[PDB]
Image: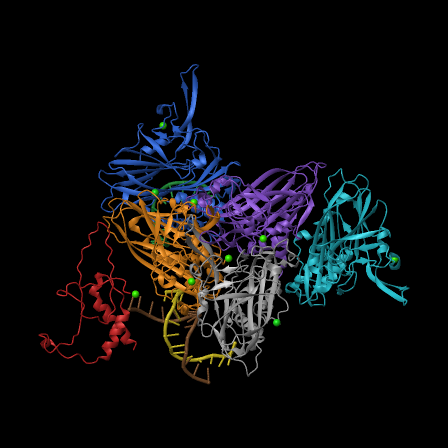
Chain colours: A red, B orange, D purple, E cyan, F blue, G yellow, H green, I brown
Amino acid sequence: GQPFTMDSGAEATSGVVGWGNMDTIVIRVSAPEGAVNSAILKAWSCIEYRPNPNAMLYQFGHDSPPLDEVALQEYRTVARSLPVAVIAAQTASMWERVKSIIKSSLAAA
Amino acid sequence: ALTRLSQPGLAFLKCAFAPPDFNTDPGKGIPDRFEGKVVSRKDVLNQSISFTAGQDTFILIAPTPGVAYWSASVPAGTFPTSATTFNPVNYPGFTSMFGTTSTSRSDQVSSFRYASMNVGIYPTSNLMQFAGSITVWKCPVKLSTVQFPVATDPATSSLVHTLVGLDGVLAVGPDNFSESFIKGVFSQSACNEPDFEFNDILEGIQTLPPANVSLGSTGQPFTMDSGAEATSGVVGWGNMDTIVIRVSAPEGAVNSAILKAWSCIEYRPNPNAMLYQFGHDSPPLDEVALQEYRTVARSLPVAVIAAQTASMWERVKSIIKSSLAAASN
Amino acid sequence: MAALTRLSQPGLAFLKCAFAPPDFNTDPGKGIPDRFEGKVVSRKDVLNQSISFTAGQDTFILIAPTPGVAYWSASVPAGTFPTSATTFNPVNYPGFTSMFGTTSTSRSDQVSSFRYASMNVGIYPTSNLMQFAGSITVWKCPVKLSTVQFPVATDPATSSLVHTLVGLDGVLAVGPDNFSESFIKGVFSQSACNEPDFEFNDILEGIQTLPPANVSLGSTGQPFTMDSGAEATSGVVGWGNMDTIVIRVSAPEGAVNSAILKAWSCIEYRPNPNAMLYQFGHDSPPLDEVALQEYRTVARSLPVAVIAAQTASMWERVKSIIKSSLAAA
Amino acid sequence: TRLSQPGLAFLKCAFAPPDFNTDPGKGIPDRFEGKVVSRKDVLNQSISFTAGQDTFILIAPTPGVAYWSASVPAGTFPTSATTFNPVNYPGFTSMFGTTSTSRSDQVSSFRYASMNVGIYPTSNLMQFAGSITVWKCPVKLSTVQFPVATDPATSSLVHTLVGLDGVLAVGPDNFSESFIKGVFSQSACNEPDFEFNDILEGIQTLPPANVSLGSTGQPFTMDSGAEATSGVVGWGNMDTIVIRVSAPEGAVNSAILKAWSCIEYRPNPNAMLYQFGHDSPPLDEVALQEYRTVARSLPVAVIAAQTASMWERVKSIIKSSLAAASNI
Amino acid sequence: TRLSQPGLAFLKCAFAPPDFNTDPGKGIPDRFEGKVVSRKDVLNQSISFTAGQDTFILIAPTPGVAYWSASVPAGTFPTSATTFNPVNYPGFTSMFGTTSTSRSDQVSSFRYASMNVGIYPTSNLMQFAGSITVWKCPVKLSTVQFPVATDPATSSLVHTLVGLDGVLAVGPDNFSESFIKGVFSQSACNEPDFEFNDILEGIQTLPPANVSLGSTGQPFTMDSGAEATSGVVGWGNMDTIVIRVSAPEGAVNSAILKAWSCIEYRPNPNAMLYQFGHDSPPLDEVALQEYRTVARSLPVAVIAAQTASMWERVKSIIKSSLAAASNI
Amino acid sequence: MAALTRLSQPGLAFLKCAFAPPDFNTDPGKGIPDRFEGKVVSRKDVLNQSISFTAGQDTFILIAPTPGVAYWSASVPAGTFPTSATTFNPVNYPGFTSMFGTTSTSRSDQVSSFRYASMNVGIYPTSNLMQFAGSITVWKCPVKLSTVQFPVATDPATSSLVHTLVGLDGVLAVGPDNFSESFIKGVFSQSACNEPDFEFNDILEGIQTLPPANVSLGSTGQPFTMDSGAEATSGVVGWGNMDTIVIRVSAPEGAVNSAILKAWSCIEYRPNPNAMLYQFGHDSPPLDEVALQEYRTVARSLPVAVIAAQTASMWERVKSIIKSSLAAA
RNA sequence: UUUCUCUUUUAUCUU
RNA sequence: UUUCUCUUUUAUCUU
RNA sequence: UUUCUCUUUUAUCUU
Ligand SMILES: [Ca+2]
Ligand SMILES: [Ca+2]
Ligand SMILES: [Ca+2]
Ligand SMILES: [Ca+2]
Ligand SMILES: [Ca+2]
Ligand SMILES: [Ca+2]
Ligand SMILES: [Ca+2]
Ligand SMILES: [Cl-]
Ligand SMILES: [Cl-]
């Protein structure tokens, strides 16, 4: 039923280790004929893993943070509030745009 | 002043002449005498599109449900010929309403009627590479039929769907908007009838002329091919004039852009459809809005540059208040 | 009140032929009060029929805007809906032949076109309290008569086009907006113009079956079939602008469900100067803005159907809605 | 309230005599205000009626064609063995080309506003004989569905005019008077609104080519002939006027026939006619209800004598109903 | 006060020209509001008058029959040796079957509202000769009682038309003018109220079969002929119009005759006509006294020229009496 | 305001066809509101033309009151003006032939006379910001069509008389009253009746060149020549009462100047009873004192030309001047 | 089809 | 296309 | 992300 295919290639270089609970961001980038479109692409991922006692990874582990009712409801609000995407320009103005939405909805409470 | 319009009657005028990027429920419906159950479908297309140099690309905003526009390119300085075929670009979820076979369109809905049909072209190329123009006019394209005989055994007479008025695309209408490509454009169409009558959903249509029909028998100047019955098709023809857009890209010109299309359509849902869940009664008659609609439409320019897409709603309100003023005297 | 005095005699009669019970409405009214005032012939069709339902079988009844035919029925296995294997047979109003002849090509001999005003139906149980069983479900489908286009491998190869009933698929599911009570409680319901205005429809020649002769159900998209039978007894003379009333009547095994079935139809025809009908014609009623807006309101206001019990209380329920909405104006 | 300039003009093109330099006007005052081109079609036809014949002239809402004429032996009406031939308005070809597929080349659709007709006897007073009779028919263009035993077997659907059977008899609502007295009559929109009808391609005959008159139900035939001189470009929503000029034996019946037609067409941007186009007049409720009233009030037809006292008949009705409604 | 829609329509069907697309209307505005079916019967008859003959046309309140015609030598009137033959309105059979006992099959009773007649000369201006004369007769359908020597001896009672002797002379109150000028005339209810009359079964001739014209008193005979083509279905309460077209020798008198008839019938539940039925209009005192007044005021008949200036004659009288009564 | 309500529908339309942009004016108006009310045919001529300018050459465009021809052009050496060695070639409005035949002696076949109402023109640059160069200068000349008288040494000797364009000499200098901005900024300008009233002008037969065939430029005084070419494609059918718009477009060497050129013409003709044109005619609009004085004022008030940019802002700029001068009255 | 308050809770029109 | 004062500085109409 | 009125116009909570 999948409309297209996903190939990670040589098992020795890449592969599909799992599938998280985050909607998938889709991006169409139209390049006309004779157009030079050069850019830098960045990607963030805050992931929390369960380290295997054997892994040379484990020594960097710690305990998950305690429940923060506030932060969780803020997260949800900010999330649903923010726009699909913004222009690269206001990437820095982002943190601020956020801090705004927080005080705005935490004020009406 | 704009308080003489019913809530919907106003909403109606907005879905109509303004690009409601604003997330209202998509339109209320039409403030006409009809108040039966309908579903206001707000169709919207966002298509990135690069224009090939040395070609005069033609785009048709037709009142064909489920399809935002049809295009094809002809060599620069020329228009479509018999040798031309237009391919449709569907709004999202075409199949989700009309199925995947030319005989399953009337499955979800039975009839329809357009309310708005807007389109905008927003240039994305730089100021050193673009070149060319965007020309726009509107054609009274209706969907009739052609009657001709066939030498079969026994010999018989045929009758098939044929598009009348297409010949209007072979020339730049006098009533037109023409300006530099880079300036983009926004334009909308309106009901080419005195009222908002419903049209039936058409089964089986995939091409015009229809398969097995020689072009010219119909008298059409070119062809319409929706392609695979499982991906697109022609489900009906609304009572809106078709919008013609000629984008001539000179040689070596990098003209890219983003095209947007809006369509408020009232469909009559079928009880067996899930879609039916979102049906409501059509808005009650709003004599004022119906009289304004007509006035606003007649006033507005053929089209305007992309920039004035915003000032659109405002331009409208002023035309209205200006009309409601003369009504007091 | 001050609402019943704003209406013209015609305007009032109109509203009665539309929602009033058959007995109260002794006067069909001079017709439809609208812009049209040409020569017409008002004919109030009424069918009374003692019918007994087949036990262990659900019987479906379709009321459609077809001139000279009250309804169409078909029985299917209990708990099921029509299938491709299903075919509906029409029951004619008295004197169908005296109106549309006896040959599929002599329908337009008496009248050329028509337009429906009211189209009601009622079921009055006559079973005793020791024999009744089952339920009566009712919903309405927006069935319209369109056309389908497809190619044919003949010699030479050609493209066809024939009549198709669009939105018939709605009959295969009980839409959320429905009436549904125990058989014994009967049911009463009407239908109204599914168009903003009352436009005339042409009389259709040669139509006997749908899909028509030599056409596979497959190529039409219609979920089931319509057969009027011998051209000499019945047939499909046209298709009006009224949503179609659908009725599922479940009869359990060993249940005696006897009832009387009634049907109303206020139709306005265009008499042919030659017809022995013409001498009964008169001019269509003048426009009655009020009556028209009342009609629309009452229509959208009334419930899908009501139990047979409150068939008489109907006229009153109506007269209520009128003063209620004409008071807030 | 009062009428608009266009709303008044509209009522004149509608029932006004054409000798009044009638203004096509800007068109029809209704909700529609779209671009359109107004055409005032006028035909003057000198014509002699065959003695011992009953000539039948039909005014139909067929664009570019003034009328269809056929003749049958005195005392009879058209039969299956009859075929009506159209007389085109001036410049038919300049509008709908010369092919049965060149109609929609200049205009895509249309709608009629008026459709009048007049017959002015030119015979002396002893030579003439016979009578003129008029009635109108609600002839509409439908479709017929019948099967055909081809390989493989198929079903055929085609155009068929309904309500023609009304021409085979003299409608009760009719005008009937001596030939010499002439006649004038007009038709009106047979629909509640003035909707647009499309232009029709390929129609040259009805029954069409390869169809028996039996398959259609139509009582007789319609032939426009050479697709290069005439044809059926569409069927409007106007009742069709029927005129039966009964000429007896040894009767010299000569006369002139005029045909009026106010039509609003939707011009194709590419057509030359587009420059002439303007916008349909704004809705004028008054005129739209006057039109409807005047129409219902006027007689089927009148002798050619009262062709000038026509406009005054109307002005009278206009203020006689603008009077029963002006009091309260 | 003013008239109702039906009360106005009623006055039009009554004296209004039929070229006005006259509305049958809902019927008669009187105390009665019962279910009925309005029928507007119209006949157009092309007819040539025998030279040296005096043709007598009688408009009688016989349903389904436009008129009865008989001819006698110029200068004479009908005699015992005369028989009048009826010309039926269209679809006579569709209403009263094909048996002398199938009349009451569709409708049980009836009552006339209007009964007009017109004659429109189609002759040229030198060929024609003669004159048209009109007067009306209070012909009513009674009964005659005479004994018959059978075994045993018995008494016989049968229908007999009274007041026919009035056709054997030209009533003083009459219209008389040149043939060519044509003529138009109408009749009115000869009773104070519009009561219903029953449909009559078995009547084909008067005197009936087996009765001598001597037994009836009737001056001449009435024959409808084949019970399968015509017959006498009833006699209404309208005075009978008499028209004497006097054609001399070598006179070519051709013309068209029209006959109007607004009738209200009580439909049988089983009849197809029942669907078309509505309720008689509510009593409209105004119209009922206007009808009565207009009637008495109007002339016996008028030349066919003033057939259109008829409606205006009425509108005039309507407000000229609504004026002598509007002051105080 | 109270100014826009004093005008008749015609009076308003008139003012728009005159100064309004081509897109806003979808309705040409019933014509000129003045004393004349006879039968006429309003024809709004519109030319759209993609034109590229020759580099290193100044191109001159002349807009004249000639029926069926939009403009006349000719290119000359940069920095220079026309000379005796110069000849202007006309560009026809669509369907010139369908109006004035194909032979210099069949111009008055469709129409006998005419009179101009509006005569606008606009230039919309389509070059990118890396390729445009040059300037657009505009002024107006009072060119009128007169006659010249001179003797001829024939046998016997005779005196001639032929058409001459008077005041053509004005095209050889940029008058103090002028528009003149960078090419890229485009330009928009109209022209108006150079007479106190709108008198009709006759259609002129046989005119193909000026100086005409067999006449030396010397004997006419005209500074340069006018050649319409093949009588079968173009020609000079008459000369209206509108000042002629002159346009100098300087294109530097190596500069890519591409633009769209538009032209308006509201002309009122006297249709010949025979013409297949006549059926579109109507009566001239009634006198509208207001509209006429407004016209004059607006005209004299508006600037020579404006940049292409404010072509839309035009209609508004106008509506301003009206209320301003109609307020002080 | 009945009666209002109350806060709702969205939604535009206006500064 | 916007707002007035001020003196401008010509210019006629009126005694 | 900013400011209120106004009528909106739906929507429940309560008598
Ligand atoms: Ca899938
Ligand atoms: Ca309609
Ligand atoms: Ca074509
Ligand atoms: Ca289907
Ligand atoms: Ca038939
Ligand atoms: Ca006697
Ligand atoms: Ca000079
Ligand atoms: Cl029964
Ligand atoms: Cl171009």
Which is more toward the observer, D219 or B127?
Answer: D219
**Image position of E31 with respect to D26: above or below:** below
**Image position of D38 with respect to F217: above or below:** below
Direction from residue E58 to residue B146 in the image, left or right: left
Q: Residue at x 54, y 41 (%)?
A: D89
Q: Is residue D70 visible?
A: yes
Quadrant of the rendering where the C terminus of chain D is positioned: bottom right
Direction from residue D272 to residue E223 in the image, left or right: right
**Image position of D218 with respect to F263: above or below:** below
Quadrant hosting ligand 8: bottom right
Residue D142 lies, in percent from the top left, at 53, 53
Residue A73 occupies which quadrant of the picture?
bottom left
Which is more toward the observer, B282 or F41?
Answer: B282
Direction from residue D219 to residue A6 in the image, left or right: left
Residue F213 lies, in percent from the top left, at 39, 24
Residue A72 occupies which quadrant of the picture?
bottom left
**Image position of E203 with respect to D262: above or below:** below
Which is more toward the observer, B36 or F221?
Answer: B36
Residue E268 lies, in percent from the top left, at 69, 66
Residue A41 occupies which quadrant of the picture?
bottom left
